């Protein structure tokens, strides 16, 4: 990952 | 709820 | 809020 | 490391 969300 | 990374 | 990120 | 919310 390395990003986030939330999807 | 709470997808992600 | 209520969502995410990271901005 | 986590601008968000
Ligand atoms: C989400 O980010 C905000 C802003 O930095 C933090 O205050 C919060 O701790 C963080 O939420 C964490 C903990 C949680 C709400 N239980 C999880 O659902 C979330 C994905 O991560
Ligand atoms: C998501 O990132 C925020 C900012 O660093 C943290 O506060 C939060 O603990 C983190 O959420 C945790 C728990 C999770 C949502 N189930 C995991 O997918 C995530 C990587 O770590
Ligand atoms: C993160 C927060 C959110 C956008 N309200 C939720 O729908 C998602 C799945 O988790
Ligand atoms: C969350 C993770 C990220 C997208 N790599 C970073 O740039 C942001 C500020 O925090």
Image (cartoon, coloured by chain):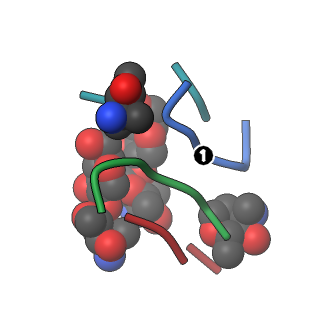
Chain colours: A green, B red, C blue, D cyan
Task: Give the image quarter of residue D1.
Answer: top left
Near mark 1 (Cα within 10 A), the count class, few <14, some 14-19 or many ≥20, is some
User: Residue at (56%, 73%) from the top-left corner?
Assistant: B2
Image label count: 1
Q: Considering only vertical position in the picture, is B5 above or below D2?
A: below
Going by the image, does C1 lie left or right of A2?
Answer: right
Q: Considering only vertical position in the picture, is A7 above or below A5?
A: below
Most foreground residue, C2 or D2: D2
User: Residue at (45%, 52%) from the top-left corner?
Assistant: A4
Going by the image, does B4 lie left or right of A7?
Answer: left
Image quarter of the N terminus of chain A: bottom left
Provide the residue designation for mark 1. C4
Going by the image, does C1 lie left or right of C5?
Answer: right
Q: Looking at this rendering, what residue extends furthest in the front direction?
A: A1
- Chain of the residue on which disc 1 is drawn: C
- Does the numbered disc 1 mark a residue whose Cβ is under 8 Å from ligand 3? yes
User: Residue at (37%, 64%) from the top-left corner?
Assistant: B5
């Amino acid at each position: 990952x390395x990003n986030x969300x939330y999807x | 709820a709470x997808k992600x990374x």
